[PDB]
Image: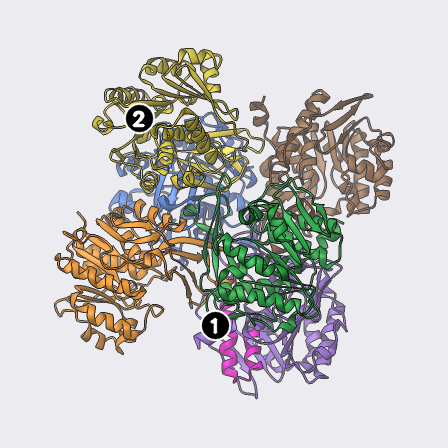
Chain colours: A orange, B green, C yellow, D blue, E purple, F brown
Amino acid sequence: MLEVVTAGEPLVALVPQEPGHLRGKRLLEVYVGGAEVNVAVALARLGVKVGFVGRVGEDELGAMVEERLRAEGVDLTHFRRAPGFTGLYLREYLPLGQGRVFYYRKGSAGSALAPGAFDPDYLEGVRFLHLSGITPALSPEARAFSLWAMEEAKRRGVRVSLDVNYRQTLWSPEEARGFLERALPGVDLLFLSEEEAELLFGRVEEALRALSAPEVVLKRGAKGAWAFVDGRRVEGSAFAVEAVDPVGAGDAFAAGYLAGAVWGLPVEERLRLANLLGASVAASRGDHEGAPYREDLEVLL
Amino acid sequence: MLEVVTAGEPLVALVPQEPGHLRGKRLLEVYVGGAEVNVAVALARLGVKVGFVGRVGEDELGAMVEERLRAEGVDLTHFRRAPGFTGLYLREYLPLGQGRVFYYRKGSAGSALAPGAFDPDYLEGVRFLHLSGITPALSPEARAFSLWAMEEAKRRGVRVSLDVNYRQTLWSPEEARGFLERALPGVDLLFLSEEEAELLFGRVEEALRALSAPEVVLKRGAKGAWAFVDGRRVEGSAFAVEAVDPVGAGDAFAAGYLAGAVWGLPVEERLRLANLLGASVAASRGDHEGAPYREDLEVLL
Amino acid sequence: MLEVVTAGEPLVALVPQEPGHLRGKRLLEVYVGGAEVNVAVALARLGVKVGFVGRVGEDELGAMVEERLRAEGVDLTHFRRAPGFTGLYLREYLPLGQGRVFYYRKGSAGSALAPGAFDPDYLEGVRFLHLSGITPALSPEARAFSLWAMEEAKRRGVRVSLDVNYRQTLWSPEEARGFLERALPGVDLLFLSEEEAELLFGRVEEALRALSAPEVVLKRGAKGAWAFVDGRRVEGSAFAVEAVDPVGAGDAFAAGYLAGAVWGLPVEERLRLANLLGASVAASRGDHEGAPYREDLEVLL
Amino acid sequence: MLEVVTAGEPLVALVPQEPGHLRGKRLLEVYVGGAEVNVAVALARLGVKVGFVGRVGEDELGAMVEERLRAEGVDLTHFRRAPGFTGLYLREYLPLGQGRVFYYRKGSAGSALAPGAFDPDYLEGVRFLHLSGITPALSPEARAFSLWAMEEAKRRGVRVSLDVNYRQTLWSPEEARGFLERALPGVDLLFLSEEEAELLFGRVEEALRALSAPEVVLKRGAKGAWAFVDGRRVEGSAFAVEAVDPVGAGDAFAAGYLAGAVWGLPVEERLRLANLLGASVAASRGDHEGAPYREDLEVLL
Amino acid sequence: MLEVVTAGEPLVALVPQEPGHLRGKRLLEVYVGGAEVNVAVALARLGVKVGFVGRVGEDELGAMVEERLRAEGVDLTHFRRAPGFTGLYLREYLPLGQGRVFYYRKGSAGSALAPGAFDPDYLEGVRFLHLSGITPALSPEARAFSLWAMEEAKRRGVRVSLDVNYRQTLWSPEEARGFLERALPGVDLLFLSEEEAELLFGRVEEALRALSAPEVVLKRGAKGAWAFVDGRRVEGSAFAVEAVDPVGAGDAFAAGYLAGAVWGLPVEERLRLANLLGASVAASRGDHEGAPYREDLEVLL
Amino acid sequence: MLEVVTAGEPLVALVPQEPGHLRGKRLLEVYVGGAEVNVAVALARLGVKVGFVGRVGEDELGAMVEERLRAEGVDLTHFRRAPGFTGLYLREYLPLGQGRVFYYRKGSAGSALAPGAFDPDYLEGVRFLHLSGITPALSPEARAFSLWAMEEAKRRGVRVSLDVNYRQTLWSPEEARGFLERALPGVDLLFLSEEEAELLFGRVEEALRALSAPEVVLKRGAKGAWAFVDGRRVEGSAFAVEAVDPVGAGDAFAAGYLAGAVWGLPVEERLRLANLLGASVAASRGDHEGAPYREDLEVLL
């Protein structure tokens, strides 16, 4: 039976082979991305039974997303290609660290996701229901899907895990705050960035007051991160590793935390695991390339 | 002074390095494409003074299209980057020959082209205004621009050259037929393929009565091509070369025919030149990569 | 329910990117191969429900073979990674056509296959059990498994399909002849090439009297192929396409013929389908890369 | 006349182009490896007259090993391809530093090497006879070859240089200790790792007591290294350079030490040279790629 | 109207893809280089109106230099291909940092440049005239061109910017001192390296006495740099970034300083800008690849 | 003892990876070339004991040429690196077939060859001395060396083989004719192409009366070739293979003919062998890459 269920819109990533302006590249690398897609893959590689709910288009790029989700062993009971196109995006990372991203996903098959996008009995028996703030920001339907989804998960006695992921492209801090204001009641585990808390609440403190979920994980760059359970406040191991491709590192972190949770580990081990996946992904090119496999944690253990 | 002026929506092409399904590729080559862009660059390489009218987005792909046109020596007096994104498309050529394309250009800055897009006096003293049937098919504003453009060209004694290029993606054979029947009177040089004639008029014979422009060039696959000028029907040289990447060959063909015209060469030479350009492009990867330079026609001469 | 079940030793292929001696290559491409693996993946792409029975080692190459089969949708109920290593082989295609292969598979986890390797009830309700003459040649345990397998299939009314594939590396024409003469009674569909018939029976005529299975398909290079069913001899379509990487073409051929059979198509269509699959693979690099997807036969239809 | 003679089994290395699990790679880089092979190449590039004794198979990979040994100028009086195959291996280096290695060398032509594998008069006049602990661990014949070899070198008044190289794949710490226990009497220069001394003697101290050769070089990660001559104990320059591909760095270190010795340099210069080669190789991909040439030491001098 | 005019000889750079001796490479990357060429491109990318004076050969490499200068938007009123060849050079960067360069430019079309190489009225209205010490060292004609050029720039009320660039391949410290001794009277902005001052004057102090131009910029490795205006001595921000390809970093630095000057910025902002471009280029492979575009400075601002 | 001795200027070839103008390539492949070098390596691969006489510069490209010759087993007794640089050249093959070359070899260490370049006694006991018409064309010193060389060879009863290879770059058909008329008496085996005969004597008929050497082989494109020996005219096998990289094919042809001669094979076999070598090279990239190994002629036999 499923331990984790994540949902969202998968994307195909087009990245250059090295630093530099995208305008000067003549070759691009292809990867499968998407916040929840990255989390599903990372969990799946760790031995966690995960299911992914979503849609891709009936095109070559959608077929690519599906092969990857299937090769990795994700459950696609409610994942399928459907009329429409698969969204993609282009990334470029500049010499001195100032990167930029371009989207071609507006109106894609996967951006659809409306309430009822799958069968709620799927969630039955599942430990977690992970979502990302990107999804509800895609369209009104998705914003509705999100709420419906976590509500149907609560109704199933399933913990809701949410990764804020404030995408300024999708919506303004106001709408973001709005959704959160409405969604927060049902979140059990909330993943937040210091910059997000600060960009949506003024300071990394106010935010910690407002968004008071049973468990909050505040990621703070290379300065470890703090996990807030039982009013207590555990700090995480900072990392002195330099970023190869920092895209997807936050997704990996979230996945490592969930894996630890799903495996009933103390908050310290959950944090140690979170940035262990986060660091691995940050250390590799691609969105979730670098995510460690079960057998790997075992050996380093 | 300019001899030719083209106009349309530039596109960035993403192409795998060898045959096979796109779902399995991990690398894509980047090329600057677009029917009119391809003609402009080919003419520019042959030494014909050419200007391209159009828009790209204010992103990295748009900047890429601009440096390309600039590097080739295309006049961009009325070409510029504007708010919005640059359209792109993916290509795939299957082992046995069956190909497929995927577009990500809907709502791009380039498909905006509406009447009055450039200063008409730009066309003054110009020999040819070149357009593609792809342009009016992008939208009603582009369909209008098309007509307005040749109207302004005709008003200035500028020969109007039109490459049908029927794209089933954009419109139906009816709307295509509709646009044609309306635009034909302003056309002086019509480039047409057999399939289109049949796909739009039943047979390569009826299409020729209906679409009777002052000079009509009918491409016939490797069976050469026929040039209908002055009740006369010049037959072109058939070529025995295998297509590497046939995509931009028709444009290279028209461009060579135009260069031949702009130079006032006999129909026999325009065809020879047209077939030459088309083959060099067909034998190369990319949309217009492979198009020869004047110095090449000098030597081969 | 499964329609076809294949079984054998998977192999990882290492191939240079262009012709030339292997001693001079600095780069090798990695592909998943294996006669039966190739058939399974081709059928899986055509929508035929197929299961592969076999073992790989508990290494990185074995994990690679497994994700591939999983990504393609091959049932692996009885396929798994086991102690030992995964066999691999290097390939080399010389400029003028003379090729050479090098094997590193002796004692691999995959060449273990012995009688009872899987639960026989797996074959229940299955249309075909596919095997290759390469399998029984790997070892006496594999030679036994082979016979046991088809015995179990026949006992279940499952049609037994066998691709001779005489590998001089593994055994002599005598042992090959010996195995054949013993296995033939349990065979319903025999795929054979002219060279093998001659290399094992003197001439492509004697081999046909001796090896008289209910349905025998004799591949004849580019001279098409003959299908001998019901005293009838259907001749196949000859193809005029140049081999890029001929290696996995025979398997693609059998797979298409099997898909045609599983779909209950006339011998003419099985051959058309078999020749189609074989050509698409021959025109591509890799062992089974190039094999078409059902959606391709839909369109070409 | 020869200054140094090394012997062992050459291997061909298959490495991915970047970090990551071998299972996800589709391209591999080819290199010539083997402990003693790496030492022979490094010495040869420094101007030291070196001979290499060994065998490769009569295959493309063996031809590759020979071209490399010959291109570099090693003496192959007793090196030749012989019936059988050339051994190979696959390496993979994980994002966070946990690498793994897979072998396909068991039963290779080069694993043969039995006593008398060459003509002992070859050693006559030679300063050193370098061997690696990998060789005697390959087979009983090789274990015999080793002892025979250094015995025939002593009998020739040739110093024996041995690099422990404890390969846990070849044999257990017990057998390792055994061989050393028997071999130690004839070793003049022994190269040891701190981890080895610790893994075979409990602590980097006990080992220093037991293995008391006229000269021992204890490599200690990036913490320089200690050279033990005349009861004295010289320490080596630590290095603050990060590992690109640390494979073969120990071989390079050994080669630089021998080059210094062979050139009659004080123990400090021998150590400075040792980690100068070690650092160069560690700084490059491949097994011995990066080994500096004579002219290089000269310039930095 | 032009803000900056630079002149010299463009070169085509052949660099390996990674560290290592050029002798072992089998693939080389192609780039457009040349001290003044690099400066012109960097200025052009920043929005500064720049013109480049020079010559390339009538070969494929010259056509490549011109496309790049044109794509980037440099003014080529006085730049053209002319009978003769385009110079090239090969670079190699060793594992531990000891690189080497090989030239094939002697007698190239661009090495010509004699007094009158262009029309002095071109300089009219221009803020700066940048030159590099490489040019006058190429030939007697060029040495003459330099003096003539800056003299004609002074006569036009144009500030002369000179980057010493002591190339020991072109001339000895004596001839270098000579030219400077004669040229110094007309230099307004002189760019100097600490090693140069030291290699041509004994110590970074004497040099500062002798070469007393209205403004001198002394580059000091990663130790920032000092700008000397009004007897005052401003220091520059040191940088803790490691060199990817340090070739052209000095040109980029010079360009950033000029851009700041051309934009009337205080000496601190000129220095901040100088090493901002310098660092970007040092951070990328190629000669001027990595040079930032206008829009980039804006965003980081 | 040596059977053949070649001599000339080695060259390093830089070639793009696919057809197209050189101005647009960003990557170049590196190959060791040189008419005589190509012959030497081909013979060396076929097992013919061969020595190459020549010089390269003391740079990285020269070291590259040397390791190549050494790796192939070419005797370099009189080959060495000397002050100066190694010549290189760029190549470009256009889509439709029109090719162009660019040289950077003037004044190289290799074009120094003057009379007395090696010890004449080196030629003793040697079957053939092979030279190319390219050599005497490099300079008067090389033109002298050429004559001196064959004079010394003839004085030793060594057969002199000469491949005209008329290079319009080096000299005119008159100077070529002049050198020929003077050298011909010392020639025993003359390799000539039809174009050269016509380009130097009007028609492939006159050239044969004038240039009447003991054995003349006239290459005739794909129309095979004629071998004129003993008033007899053996016609060679025409080949129906498409040129991949035709550049070094003529040398591969001569080399095979020479190997055939050195082995004392009938003219029919020399031609068969010559055509075989030429085709294998024509079908491969590089100057002499593709040339077969003896073990290949063994198997194809």
Q: Name the residue under label 2.
A: C129
Q: Nearer the viewer, mark 1 or mark 2?
A: 2
Q: In this view, does B60 lie above or below C187?
A: below
Any magenta on residue E72?
A: no
Quarter assignment of residue C188: top left
User: As drawn, is D278 to the left or to the right of F279?
Assistant: left
Determine whether the residue tagged by mark 2 lies in a helix, strand or loop. Answer: strand
Q: Where is residue E81 in the image (x, y as percent from the top left)?
A: 71, 62
**Same-subunit check for callouts 1 and 2:** no
How crowded pointer 2 is (Cα within 10 Å; few <14, some 14-19, many 20+) is rated as many
Q: What residue type is labelled 1?
A: Asp
Q: Which amino acid does label 2 sit on?
A: Leu
Q: Which residue is drawn at 48% across and 26% down?
A: D82
User: As drawn, is B153 to the left or to the right of D215?
Assistant: right
Q: Where is residue E78 in the image (x, y as percent from the top left)?
A: 71, 70
Q: Name the residue under label 1.
A: E296
Report whether residue F278 is seen: yes
Q: Is the magenta stretch mostly helix, strand or loop?
A: helix
Determine whether the residue tagged by mark 1 lies in a helix, strand or loop. Answer: helix
Whole-angstrom CA distance, mark 1 to mark 2, is 63 Å
Q: In this view, does E157 lie above or below A55?
A: below
Instruction: Using the image as rendered, state which of residue C258 and residue F187 is in the foreground.
Output: C258
Instruction: Using the image as rendered, state which of residue A276 and residue C145 is in the foreground.
Output: C145
Query: What is the span of residues highlighted in magenta in the rendered image?
Result: E255-283
Any magenta on residue E256?
A: yes
Please give the chain letter of the residue carrying mark 2.
Answer: C
Please give the chain letter of the residue carrying mark 1.
Answer: E
Q: Position of residue B108 (x, y in %)?
A: 47, 64
